[PDB]
Image (cartoon, rainbow over all chains, first blue to last red):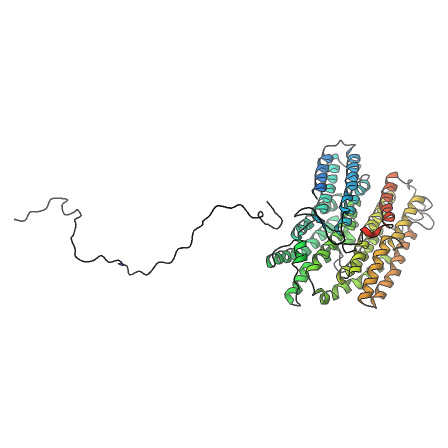
Amino acid sequence: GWVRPDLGELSKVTKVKTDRPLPENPYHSRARPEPNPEVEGDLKPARHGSRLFFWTM
Amino acid sequence: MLKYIIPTMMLMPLTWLSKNSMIWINTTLHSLLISLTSLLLLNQFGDNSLNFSLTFFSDSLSTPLLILTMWLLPLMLMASQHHLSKENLARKKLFISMLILLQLFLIMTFTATELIFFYIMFEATLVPTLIIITRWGNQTERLNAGLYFLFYTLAGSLPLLVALIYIQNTMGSLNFLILQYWVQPMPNSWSNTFMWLACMMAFMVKMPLYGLHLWLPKAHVEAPIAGSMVLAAILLKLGGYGMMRITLLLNPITDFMAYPFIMLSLWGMIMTSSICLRQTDLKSLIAYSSVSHMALVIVAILIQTPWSYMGATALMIAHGLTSSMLFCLANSNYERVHSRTMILARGLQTLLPLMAAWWLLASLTNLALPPSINLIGELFVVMSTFSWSNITIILMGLNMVITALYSLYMLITTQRGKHTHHINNILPSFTRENALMSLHMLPLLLLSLNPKIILGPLY
């Protein structure tokens, strides 16, 4: 009394109840590098113009 | 200095909107009015410079040069309004436009607060002079003179640009006041050797230094009268003003560096003066006289003593006025006789008495007759150089002979002797020429009374 499965029955995804713990580091990866800091604060106006050897504006 | 630039920028449409018969009168009137208003820069101090804004300032050094420039431009318009009477209206207006643009360029260059602005304006002064020389010149080979002038100036001034940008990137600024307060000594190293050479060679080219003076006996001859005056009376003093500004930044290396260059003048101004003893072209004689005076200026600036500075600026102003007057005299005689040969026109006193009087006055002011400004400047230079060393008095004293030995010679052959027979087109003196020469001469004799305004920044 074993039933031959229909088309599409074996092609579906099932669930498993497993007693093993989840590995936190499957790739054996070290710590990622620290990201560079972002920009903060209000966009202040230009200090004394463009300063291109004589320009004040 | 925005009270003088805007009047010139308004003079530009003033010569682009007048009629074909009223350009000269309107331009002369308004340029003389600007010359009258130019005297407000004399509000100077014995210890501070007159600063207007972040870009323009004027101490007691640039002020006489500014006054001379915008006093010379109306004289230029008078001197160049006869030989261009046959030209097209568009080309005449273009000539006046180039002269006005050149005056604007000079008055913007002489008041430059920071040195990079002075450099770019100093190279920007090339364009109208080159255009005038290569367009309105008379002789065939004027293209060679224009190319020589432009290339000598550019090959001098590009290492000056590299050195200026290097100095700005090194210390932080190029303001003259800041550099006066943030100056640093330069040690005796080969890097500082090439820094001194790059900062000096442009000004030694435009002075011109002996050896590199070959652009003067051509570009002073084939150019017209206005181009000759702007080459003889302004641009050499532009180079001198630049050297005076720069030499503050190059201590104490110059005290052991300027030994050849000074002496490259201290002999050269002898033999170039001797060239005036054997010259067949009058304009070349005037140009070589200018070479000798600028060599004296080179010695005075390079020894960097105070009395030398005062003599340098006084001789600058006096020699500029005298050389402009002599170039006008050469142009008038060339217009009358259609030849630049000095030996051709003789005995002009018997035909032109007033012109002979002007010739005598110009020759006397050229040989440093006291109490004119030229004698004051050259005497101060001689005192300073005698303080520097003893034997150099000989190297000046013999020049005291040779200058006279050509100048009165220039007075003799053109004026004294039996007049030429086949020359019979010597017209009487034009009122324009007499007015121009009186406007050249009378300010010099008036400044002989009160020279204290043209004796430099440290009087």
